[PDB]
Image (tube, rainbow, N blue to C red; front, side, top):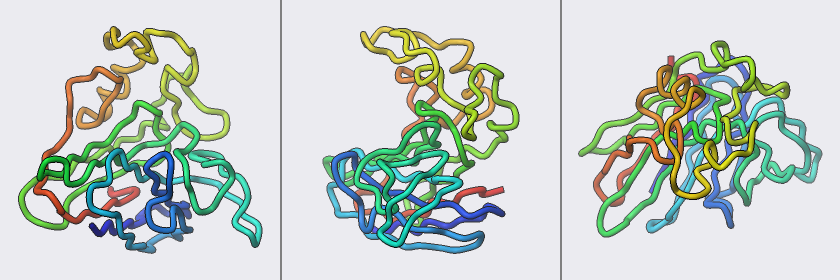
Length: 206
């Protein structure tokens, strides 16, 4: 499957693509404002994620640091990124279908649209100014809006027991972005697409 990753932000981002235990494609690349990077994701990929990283520095070997979404200091991510990260999440060719969503469960750093480029389903979008409106207690000093689990480490926020409800913090994410997950047990906003669809992830869609 192809994923065209497009940076419409006015700032550079470093795109990242991983399934947690391995890179997807090259795993990461710089995207200056307006640039597009097309990756190939193996069919059957389960639990893939794409995100943006901000304010990154890499040496000639591809080692460094990002303020948001850092994946073990690598340009080419092999693992998931450090919150806060708005997440484009996907599982492909799962009993003949693809499943896509956006999640704010690991916080928000950059607004995102995640849409098919092929027929048969709709896209999802989280493009509100979550950083600007972020509750004081969730503001990440390194940049972005943390989720409550990252900040407070409670069973309730982290859904450790598989019993948890919405919270004042999850309702903030859900108010600003109804079509993204706001907490682990949120009413799903997953979209079912035909198996082997292709996609575009657009940072800063509006």
